[PDB]
Image (cartoon, rainbow, N blue to C red; front, side):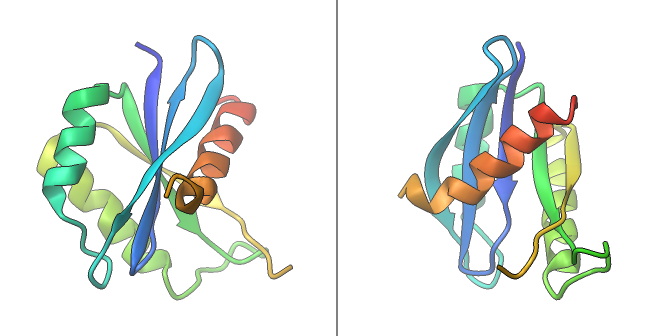
Length: 120
């Protein structure tokens, strides 16, 4: 299909974006609340049945030198649980970021756009 979902892990909120390869674009969906990084999996399940993504992307936050940040490990755990519970291919995409509703998903849109621009 060329349809993809991206998630921006957070402990209180997880951003969501849906993207289309055919048109090469990404757009935000309403963020998902989390309780210490745990969402209401029914929401994630609904998104997967509704969009049938060819694969899903999860941002792997790192430092500008590529070292791991505090959330890196949680982000990864989150990524494995999606894959584990749903079987869809999940891909971690290095989120190299620096210290410088759908609006709460802005970071998920950037993660997905970057993933397309880098040729993945």
